[PDB]
Amino acid sequence: TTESLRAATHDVLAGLTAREAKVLRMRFGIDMNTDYTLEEVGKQFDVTRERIRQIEAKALRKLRHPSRSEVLRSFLDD
DNA sequence: TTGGTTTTTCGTGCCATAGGTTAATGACTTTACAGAGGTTACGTTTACATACATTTGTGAATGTATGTACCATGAACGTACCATAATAGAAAGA
Image 1 (cartoon, rainbow, N blue to C red):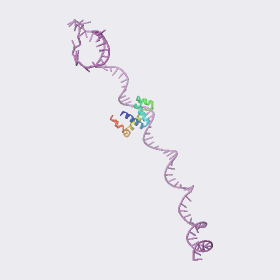
Image 2 (image 1 turned 90 degrees about the vertical axis):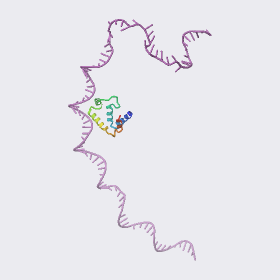
Image 3 (image 1 turned 60 degrees about the vertical axis):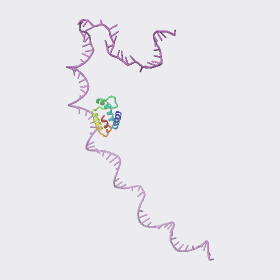
Image 4 (image 1 turned 120 degrees about the vertical axis):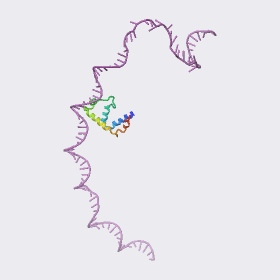
């Protein structure tokens, strides 16, 4: 189920916008070693840090839809 | 008396005078594409107040730390079932 969840999250990040995928990977430590903080993401990508939170809120609003997470609703019990 | 060349009408074929539907480019006109201009509702960038965390001192839990000065003089301090046959070892008589 972990190996299937990896491919499922890879397909979800590939189905969305590529820059959204890079933010969601380098934010929580997906496909990286360390999880970068908000100041480190601000030093890497762009100075504005409130727009990063707006991007995160927009990504959560796009990922609350059941049609894009119907294969992930079965993984909710784990 | 019978076959075949000759000749003239007559409906049919060729030529000419009339008169009408319908090809031409166009001129259409209608639909489609191309031009700017005012308005909407976002998306990114910026400052500011308050919060969980994380960084410090301070009161209690244990823990090794060295000694106690009538006389204490050898034992296993209770273990245990005793199968079977290849290969060497330390001696004993040949």
